[PDB]
Length: 5
Length: 250
Length: 28
Ligand SMILES: CCc1cc(OCC(C)(C)CN(C)C)cc([C@@H](Nc2ccc(C(=N)N)cc2)C(=O)O)c1
Ligand SMILES: [Ca+2]
Ligand code: NA
Image (cartoon, rainbow over all chains, first blue to last red; front, side, top):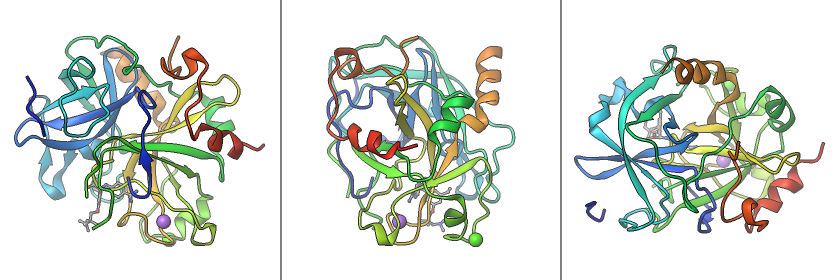
C-alpha cells in the first residue's frame, strides 16, 4: 500500500 | 471478488475500506450509511477463533476509493473511529449468525461525487426485492481467486438463491438472519465474494424509486466461487431494529 | 433523503454498464 499522509 | 469486473468511477460511492494501521493492509469491506455511521460484518472486528479483536485505534476508514493500493489524493477521505458497536447476539462460536457491526466516525465525512450513503431497506423493500432469482451487486477489494489482488474495486452481480438450495449446499446451520447468493452449476455464469470482501455491501436497485438499498453484508463462504457452493450474506432488514437502536441511542 | 442516489449516475440520469441486468431479474 502507498503511504498515507 | 472472483469472476467479477472493474468498477466504474463512482459506481459504489458508499464503498468503504477498513484499513489496518499496523501492518498496513486491507482488513475488510464496509459501507457508508450516513455522514457519521459505517456498516460492516462483526467478524471483521471480532473473531476469537483467529485471535482477532480490533479496537477503535487499530484501524482507519477509507471512503471514496477506487484503486486498492494508491493514496487517492483529492478523492478519498480518511476517517478515524470513535466507537465500534458489535451486535450483542453475534454468534462467532458456530455459524456467524447476526454477523453485523456499526462504527461511528470521529467527525462527519463530506459527501462528494465519490462519497455518498446507501439506503437501508424497510419491510416493504425487503419483501419486494429479497426473492430467489432477483440479482444484487457485491463489491470489494478482496482476492480475485480462492488460491491475486485487484488493482481497482471489483463488482459482480449475483442472483439470490432459494433457501432450501442454500441449506442443501452446506453442513453449516443457516439462520433466518442469513441469505445466500450465486449462480448454480447449471446456470453457466460464475462469481463470488472472497477473502478480503467480508463486511462489504450486497446492494439492489429498487425498480420503484430508482434508489440503491443495502440488502446484505458479505459474511462467509466455503472457499470462493466453487460449483454447488454459495456466498452467505447477513440479512440487513432482519437486523434493522438493532441498527436503529444503536444510532438512536448513540 | 438523498440516500442511494449516486452523484455520477442517478443524480445525472446516467446508467452504469450492468444495472440493467439487475432490473431484468426483477420480474414479479
Ligand atoms: C470467519 C468466517 C470465515 C471463514 C473462512 O474460511 C476460512 C478457511 C476456509 C480458509 C479456513 N477455515 C477452515 C479456518 C473465510 C472467511 C473469509 N470471508 C469470506 C467471505 C465470503 C466468502 C465467499 N462468499 N466465498 C468466503 C470467505 C474471511 O473473512 O477471511 C470467513
Ligand atoms: Ca444442510
Ligand atoms: Na458457487
